[PDB]
Image: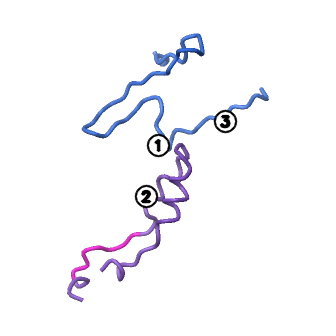
Chain colours: A purple, B blue
């Protein structure tokens, strides 16, 4: 309660780390699929 | 004026295309190959 009261982190959508590394296709294709399967969605109620 | 980086040097034997780059305090930007997007890999086709 005390922490989330200060809203230190709000969440935006479309994680950049997956926006990029998606549309350039000039690297080893496991970095894909692996970073691609690790990035789960996030809603601050887990951050806080 | 446009063409200055030579494309080849004859024999496909000891060529090793240009390897200049800029260093910017750790960060490095090559000039001949960079997997960053906006550099569309060309789809050439023998059928010509």
Q: Position of residue A10 (x, y in %)?
A: 32, 74
Secondary structure, mark 1, is loop
Residue B42 position, x and y percent, is: 62, 34
- Residue extending farthest to the right is B47
Answer with mark 3 or mark 1, whichever residue precedes in sequence: 1
Q: What segment is highlighted magenta in the picture?
A: A6-12
Callout 3: chain: B
Residue B18 within the magenta-colored segment of the rendering: no
Give the spatial CA distance, label 3 vs label 1.
Answer: 17 Å
Q: Residue at x 54, y 53 (%)?
A: A30
Q: Is residue B28 above or below residue B4?
A: below
Mark 2 against mark 3, which lies toward the viewer?
2
**Labels 3 & 1 near each other (Cβ < 8 A):** no
Mark 2 — on which chain does it sit? A
Q: For the point 42% across and 29% down, which residue is it?
A: B31
Q: Where A41 sits versus B36, above or below?
A: below
Disc 1 from disc 2: Cα separation: 13 Å
Q: Secondary structure at mark 3?
A: loop
Answer yes or no: are tags 1 and 2 on the same subunit: no
Q: Is residue A42 left or right of residue B25?
A: right
Residue drawn at x 46%, y 73% is A41
Circle 2 is placed at which residue position?
A17
Disc 3 with disc 1 on a shared chain: yes
Using the image as rendered, state which of residue B4 and residue A2 is in the foreground: A2
Residue beneath label 1, please? B36
Q: Mark 2 to mark 3: distance in Å?
A: 27 Å
Query: Which residue was labeled with disc 3?
Result: B43
| Residue A19, percent from left and from top | 48, 57
Circle 1: is it few (<14), some (14-19), or many (20+) Cα within 10 Å?
some
Image quadrant occupied by the N terminus of chain B: top left
> Which residue is nearer to you in this view: A1 or B13?
B13
């Amino acid at each position: 309660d005390y922490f989330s009261q200060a809203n230190v982190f709000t969440v935006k959508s479309e994680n950049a780390i997956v926006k990029m590394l998606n549309s350039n296709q000039n690297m080893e294709p496991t970095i894909i699929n692996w970073f691609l399967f690790r990035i789960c969605a996030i809603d601050k109620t887990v951050i806080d | 004026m446009q063409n200055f980086i030579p494309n080849t040097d004859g024999q496909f034997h000891s060529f090793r295309a240009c390897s200049y780059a800029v260093k910017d305090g750790g960060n490095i930007y090559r000039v001949v190959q960079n997997g960053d997007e906006l550099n569309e890999s060309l789809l050439i086709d023998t059928a010509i």
